[PDB]
Image (cartoon, rainbow, N blue to C red; front, side, top):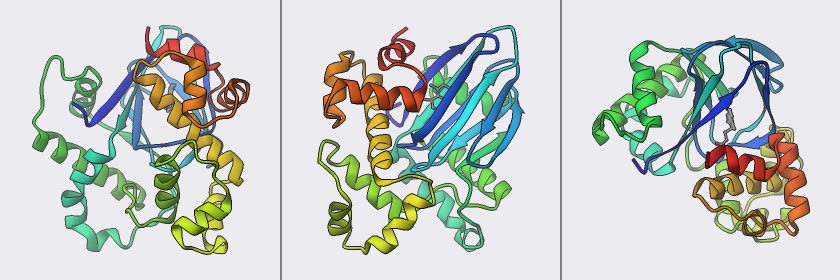
Length: 269
Ligand SMILES: Cc1cccc2c1[C@@H](CCC(=O)O)CCC2
């Protein structure tokens, strides 16, 4: 069970979630349970409709800019699964046992879509229900998720499970290992022993400057702390490395379109 962190958000008619410079700290997937939603991806400048069988995948270490809008009147529950790095790395012996195909894939897609059948959605639902009803062996989930990811990578002809030595993974592991450190460019270069010229590409490829990058990682770090049931916003701001509650709230509102305490309540309730 520890391999997954899950949440279910309610969404009334024609209301919209809006995410800007949302940093994806760990592999995430989401789907709606009924009705129709509109997804506008500002990174790919595309909009499209999703239904109860559309699974949307967000790649680890991407910077997401999209909105999700309900086009139903009946309320909609959005389920989100965050997959722990421990579990992702246990899959490697399944995805990369098929590596000669995988070298020919590209690395441009951060938000992937899968139209699946009922069984796939029954499995992910039970994941979202904390396996209260059906329990699943570690081998079943490893086979299921590795097979799921390789189907989606095949569809887009692009790698989804990145590898450890990717520059942006090194930057982001480093920042997350010491969230309250006063990070500057010079620290990244010195820890990774890598020229600014080369590391720079990972931030411009994602449309961020250094400050918005650090801020996005800290917002996700703070969202992770809110999910643990820690409830004090003032503590969460300082624990996530911000210098004031005001600055944390301003960045949070800019990223999530909701105030930190509004989000903290969407979790515990
Ligand atoms: C709050 C929400 C509602 C609907 C969809 C999505 C979200 C957040 C999930 C928050 C997280 O896990 O950090 C971002 C990904 C997709």
